Image: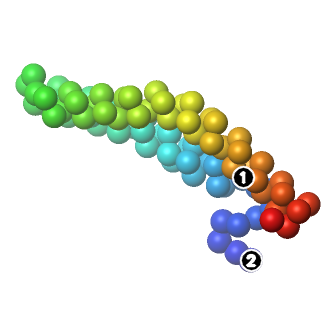
Amino acid sequence: GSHMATPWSGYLDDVSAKFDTGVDNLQTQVTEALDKLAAKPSDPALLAAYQSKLSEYNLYRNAQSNTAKAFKDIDAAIIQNFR
């Protein structure tokens, strides 16, 4: 068959890679950033690190949610319009 490339999929694996692995990665990264922040005393980088992942994560929930929609939609044209 093929590698990650099926019709009417989008969430079958595409979006899921940016949603599950993507967001799950952003959710576990701050966890590391957590054990890492408490690792070093009051530090600029460690704290900035968990936050850097935070601001990107909180926005992630909205972005990935607004990007996945148009993503699965474009495929709808590759079958009816062949795009």
Can the viewer see residue 11? no
Query: At 69% across and 49% down in the image, what residue appears?
Result: 71
Query: At 91% across and 60% down in the image, what residue appears?
Result: 80
Can the viewer see residue 72? yes
The residue carrying mark 2 is 1
Mark 1 crowdedness (10 Å alpha carbons): few <14, some 14-19, many ≥20: many
Distance between the alpha carbons at the discs numbered 2 and 1: 17 Å
Residue positioned most to the right: 80
Q: Describe residue 44's horizontal placement relative to residue 82 as left or right.
A: left
* Percent coordinates x, y for residue 69 in the rendering: 71, 41
The residue carrying mark 1 is 10
Tag 2's secondary structure?
loop
**Residue 13 picture quarter:** bottom right
Q: Nearer the viewer, residue 19 or 56?
A: 56
Q: Quadrant of the C terminus?
A: bottom right
Q: Which kind of residue does numbered mark 1 sit on?
A: Gly
**Residue 57 picture quarter:** top left
Tag 1's secondary structure?
loop
Between marks 2 and 1 in the image, the one whose residue lies nearer the viewer? 1
Residue positioned most to the bottom: 1
Q: Describe residue 12's horizontal placement relative to residue 59 as left or right.
A: right
